[PDB]
Length: 77
Length: 74
Ligand SMILES: [Mg+2]
Ligand SMILES: [Mg+2]
Ligand SMILES: [Mg+2]
Ligand SMILES: [Mg+2]
Ligand SMILES: [Mg+2]
Image 1 (cartoon, chains in turn brown, yellow):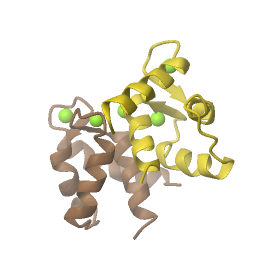
Image 2 (spheres, chains in turn yellow, blue; image 1 turned 90 degrees about the vertical axis):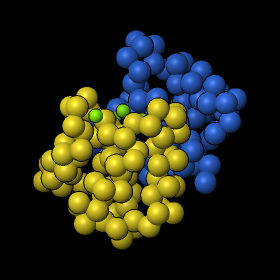
Image 3 (cartoon, chains in turn purple, red; image 1 turned 60 degrees about the vertical axis):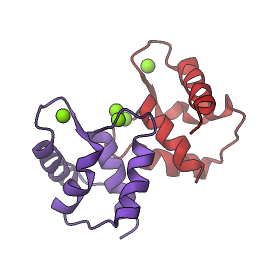
């Protein structure tokens, strides 16, 4: 899985983009947060990720969802 | 996801989220999927669980279930 250090680091990055502190970020920020952590998903990969995480159409990504996407992205690096 | 599918998924999720906190546990994912007429293998379930439960809390909420169903359909 992910370590407790990886989770802490991902949470710090995530926190930088949740500027209202409500626990979510917009899907429009996913690429930016991933790039801040050194990942460089293509626009196609990013759009696929967004369609999936945003299946409910609320346009929100929360921290467990971000970890899931990082975890999925790290199985494919 | 069609509106029908989303509706079917929400009905299924609700079958298990009887306390209404919008959350079920990872232990229940297999049974939820069976309620939809699917018979995922233990290996498939472990794969889904390891991903959605990256944070180690053992919890699945409804948006996550939808995402998992969407990802399983690809
Ligand atoms: Mg926010
Ligand atoms: Mg959301
Ligand atoms: Mg519940
Ligand atoms: Mg959870
Ligand atoms: Mg959530």
